[PDB]
Image (cartoon, rainbow, N blue to C red):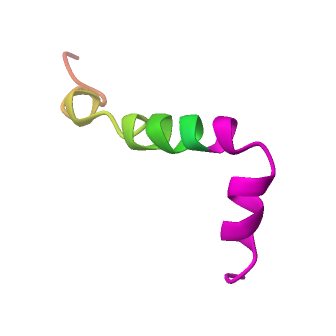
Amino acid sequence: GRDAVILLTCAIHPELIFTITKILLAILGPLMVLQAGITK
């Protein structure tokens, strides 16, 4: 749940989880959404 994971996120491999959050926002792909099953 909460009130524990946030503490473990900054205490256990914080330099790696932050990088995942940055890629998490880039995993959507606003341009890719306009190319799903296109040009057929």
Query: Residue 29's quadrant in the figure?
Result: top left
Instruction: Give percent across and percent down for residue 25.
Output: 39, 43
Compare residues 22 and 34 and report the one nearer the observer. Answer: 22
Q: Quadrant of the N terminus?
A: bottom right
Q: Dominant secondary structure of the magenta stretch?
A: helix
Q: Is residue 16 above or below residue 38?
A: below
Whether 18 is among the magenta residues is no
Q: Quadrant of the C terminus?
A: top left
| Most distant residue in the top direction | 39
Instruction: Give percent across and percent down for residue 35.
Output: 24, 26
Left or right: residue 5 versus residue 38 is: right
Q: Is residue 12 above or below residue 22?
A: below
Whether 2 is among the magenta residues is yes
Which residue corresponds to the image point at 23% horizontal and 36% vertical from the top-left?
Answer: 30
Compare residues 2 and 35 and report the one nearer the observer. Answer: 2
Q: Is residue 14 above or below residue 32?
A: below
Please state the extent of the stretch shown in magenta in the rendering.
1-17
Q: Is residue 12 above or below residue 2?
A: above
Which residue corresponds to the image point at 77% horizontal and 62% vertical from the top-left?
Answer: 8
Left or right: residue 37 versus residue 10 is: left
Left or right: residue 21 versus residue 33 is: right
Query: Residue 10's quadrant in the figure?
Result: bottom right
Q: How many marks?
A: 0
Query: Residue 14's quadrant in the figure?
Result: top right
| Most distant residue in the right direction | 12
Instruction: Give percent across and percent down for residue 9.
Output: 70, 57
Which residue corresponds to the image point at 22% horizontal and 23% vertical from the top-left?
Answer: 38
